[PDB]
Image 1 (cartoon, rainbow over the protein chains, first blue to last red):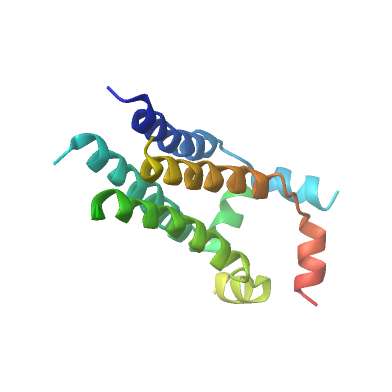
Image 2: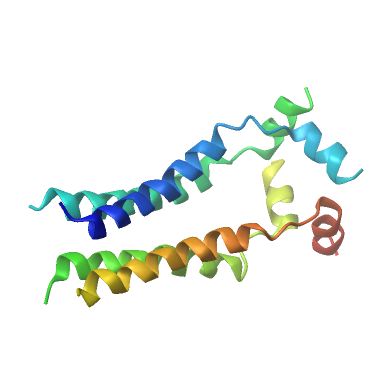
Length: 38
Length: 38
Length: 38
Length: 38
């Protein structure tokens, strides 16, 4: 195989897994307004 | 062709397609506020 | 010359170009709210 | 020794360092609304 190209391929699926992983968050519009305007 | 590079290339145009398509996700700012505040 | 791997390199400087191209300006709070509440 | 893949390899970890580096940048709902609505 080739750990050099494979390594990079993982760096890509990394930025992706990071985006969708953080998206599954339900977040909250009330927590942002009451926590932002204190 | 070489599925390793060809694949990674696609994984790139993917993270991109996901960035812009996710940006258009937002649309009705009035509904979102009527879904969280209520 | 290898347009396949080279093409990818450009796809990278692309995702970067975009991110910063929008940072310069693309929010507009008075426009998204006056046109968001419809 | 392959300067073509190695080169992009650095451009990739760059988009990453620049992505997370820009993320640590916090903000404020009262600052963007008092500076944007003005």
